[PDB]
Amino acid sequence: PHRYKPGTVALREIRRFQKSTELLIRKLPFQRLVREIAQDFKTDLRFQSSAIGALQESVEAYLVSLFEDTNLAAIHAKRVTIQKKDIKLARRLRGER
Amino acid sequence: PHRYKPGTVALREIRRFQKSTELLIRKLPFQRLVREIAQDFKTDLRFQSSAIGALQESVEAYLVSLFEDTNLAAIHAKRVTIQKKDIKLARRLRGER
Amino acid sequence: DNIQGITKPAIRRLARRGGVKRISGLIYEETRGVLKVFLENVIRDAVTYTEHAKRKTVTAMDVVYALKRQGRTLYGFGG
Amino acid sequence: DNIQGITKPAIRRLARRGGVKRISGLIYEETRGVLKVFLENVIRDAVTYTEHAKRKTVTAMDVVYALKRQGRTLYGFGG
Amino acid sequence: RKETYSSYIYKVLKQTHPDTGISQKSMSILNSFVNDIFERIATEASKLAAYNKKSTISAREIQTAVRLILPGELAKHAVSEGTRAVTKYSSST
Amino acid sequence: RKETYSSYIYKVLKQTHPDTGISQKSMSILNSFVNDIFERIATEASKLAAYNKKSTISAREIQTAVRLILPGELAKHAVSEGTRAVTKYSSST
Amino acid sequence: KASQSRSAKAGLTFPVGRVHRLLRRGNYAQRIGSGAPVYLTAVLEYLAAEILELAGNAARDNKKTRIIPRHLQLAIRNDDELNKLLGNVTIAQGGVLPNIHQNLLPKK
Amino acid sequence: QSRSAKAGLTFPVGRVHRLLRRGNYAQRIGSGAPVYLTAVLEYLAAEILELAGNAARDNKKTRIIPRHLQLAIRNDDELNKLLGNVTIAQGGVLPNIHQNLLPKKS
DNA sequence: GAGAATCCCGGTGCCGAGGCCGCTCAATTGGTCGTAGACAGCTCTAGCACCGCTTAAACGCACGTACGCGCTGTCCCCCGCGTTTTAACCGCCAAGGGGATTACTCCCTAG
DNA sequence: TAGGGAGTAATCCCCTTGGCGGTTAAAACGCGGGGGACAGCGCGTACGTGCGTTTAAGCGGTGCTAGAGCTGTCTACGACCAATTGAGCGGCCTCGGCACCGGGATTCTC
């Protein structure tokens, strides 16, 4: 059969994901995560679905901006594969410690 | 015939300026610079003496805060010498464009 | 299985939204770690706005005010 | 030639404050181009405060408020 | 009873694009945007009036706040539109 | 005829340290610190009062404010000492 | 005796009196002058008109007749003074502009 | 009788009440609220003065200098991120030397 | 093993950091009233819980190949140092231009 | 309808912009030398690809009840006003901590 070069259909997946505007995290594991993370500060806490959407949009923008910052720090380091020290450098030079 | 290794006296004077906290910028050339950069909008400008000292402290703090960041970018770049590309990545990661 | 409630291709989806090419395997738990240190700072401020208002449910208002605080503001839910 | 007011050993003094063993020679003019935009960005918000005060002199009182407006609030000269 | 700007901005869109529809979420973003802009401009003006030891807000402190906040060509177009509007309104004679 | 805070910080410093001297640049520094903390706390308290449809500022809103901005062990130290002062005032009414 | 509002006296479609109300009981100042709501209303007029212009051109650029938040996001992020003003705000359901680094392409 | 002495504090409750009421924050204002703000300002002032005093005695001086103030603010991490956006005057930077920049071996 | 280069101990004006009195506004006390915060009480939206079908998304094992990484040889461009030289800085004298402030007034903004 | 907040303006005094000049740390400039950055080449493995096999997300439907939210009523906290006393700003006065200078011990570096 006919195959593809590794890193060429990944460009197509990149342009598909950078066209598509849809949501990239499933709603029930995220709502379980935010409920068990809000249980620590205060019990018997109910939630709103609009608050769920606002929270998920905030964290989705946060990983997106942090992630091209990590990618730019990685190509800065004459490499293509990202590593954990790129994340630590991006966090340290972005200001949050 | 006593010749020092290059960088040892650099680190020693780095230590002396680490105990030091005085102004490292000459006063009158910086006064000339701020007058020639403030003349362009409304001429015949009177200046107070303390404003120039405040400008000195702010430019020195911004320079050292950028230089620690580009030192971190340089030591992350597996090098000892800095470059313009470290300075651009410092400005990109700190976010002043 | 709550902190790993997000799945392995979820960081991949957030990755390829970000224009990356090659991704390692040790970064997934580290991205989950920055999830933890981000959501603590978000929902501690959210629950301060919550029980200040004498309510035991979070609405759409206190979350966007919590987001308004640190300078990562978000539109769309301002009303 | 007045733009040549800032001198290269002063940039070296600022560099060794950062604790750097090796400095290349292009860093001086890079920092010159960096600083030139930077001080003009506070001269932008100082002289308009001065003009709205109906004053033709600047002081230590409006420059600290310009830095406090942009977001590097500085102590020592009041405010 | 709740307040929104929706009919005014709808009319602004019909002045330049008559055949264009609207998502309600787009009104939510743009209402938040105009409220946020009014927010920063108004507290910048109040802060500047508290600086000059004045108890009155007039057109000149919000003019200076517009010059402070907006970028330069938007600042000059905004003060042009504001000055022509306030001189048209001031001609009530 | 300006107002300073120098006598009170001098009294506090002599309460904690009976031998330390101080310079005037440091007094300007920490007067600016006190005014910055006061101003940030005050605009946050006014914001939380206007946000809860509330026309009076009472100690609950500054309690929520010093909960939300100040660091946590300083936050509960400040809450403890401020509540101690609150009961000291309400006892000695 | 009957006369209309100040908005058409200034020739504006945004409410001058509502802005005056919000400036009065928004506790920004103890005294509010007459010409301040007119100036602020005109500034909001021009800002909303320019944002609607860029949104309408973006919606024409996708061959649609409705304003999607994608159109608002691309109109804000494409243009650079709107990039500087709105850099710190994340648009709800906006997405990310397409960009690839030159070294990441299959250069060969 | 002074309200500061009634509340057991050494800070001018009347002055901060004046600054709060003629500062245009709310139409009405509380009575125990300036006392509460007075107490928390006294606490932060006392704690930063204690830290500056310790940073004075460890470097043999009986005088407070802004370098000692920088030494007092930067070591405490919670105070450091409290003032992560604040530039001090005549304070300097802490001495940190990178391990890769440190030469030789052992 | 030597040698710059530090750290450490002792004498010196000094000039800038603690008291002190004078006193002038600004914190304190008392009375009045009209409204706003608190509590009680009320109606329904909306949030939680669970059952069950569908299935597309996710885990896991297998392998193959670019890409991270270790080593290497090399220009060469930064680093220590001697020599001019050039502008920065300190002491100072004089001007006059610009900020502070007093003082009445009227208009326009609060109600 | 009212009243008090800018507005005008004049006057005093203070600081700051030029202009002196010496002298002196300090920058400019040229020169020897040494590790550091540069590309290049090989070794292996880790991430991409793929198919079989779950699984537990998603829809959607229903049932229940807390709790959001609006209204009514009350009364006591607080703005407002008039008199008062005291305390914190300031000019003035006085003296010792620290920088500065001089000279000897001491530690990395070569």
Image (tube, coloured by chain):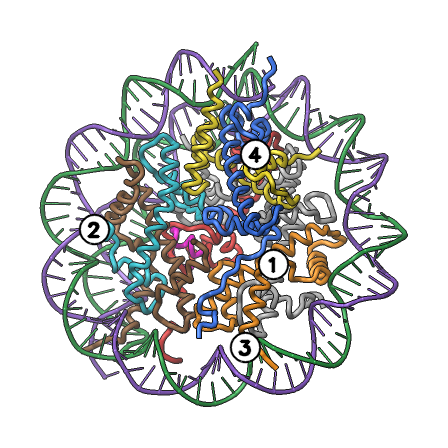
Chain colours: A orange, B brown, D cyan, E yellow, G blue, H red, I purple, J green
Residue corresponding to mark 2: D1
The label nearer to you, 2 versus 4, is 2
| Residue stretch rendered in magenta on the structure | H58-72
Q: Same chain for the residues at labels 3 and 1, yes or no? A: yes
Q: Are marks 2 and 4 in contact (CB under 8 Å)?
A: no
Q: Are marks 3 and 4 in contact (CB under 8 Å)?
A: no
Residue corresponding to mark 1: A60
Q: Residue type at mark 4: give it.
A: Tyr
Q: Secondary structure at mark 2?
A: loop
Residue corresponding to mark 4: H25
Q: Same chain for the residues at labels 1 and 4, yes or no? A: no
Label 3 is found on which chain of the structure? Answer: A
Q: Residue type at mark 3: give it.
A: Lys
Toward the viewer: A16 or I49?
A16
Magenta segment: does it hold H99? Answer: no
The label nearer to you, 3 versus 2, is 3
Magenta segment: does it hold H61? Answer: yes
Image quadrant holding the N terminus of chain H, namely top right
In the rendered view, would you say J41 is above or below E80?
below
Location of residue J55 in the rendering, given as x and y in whole percent from the top left corner: 77, 71
Q: CA distance from mark 3 to mark 2?
A: 57 Å
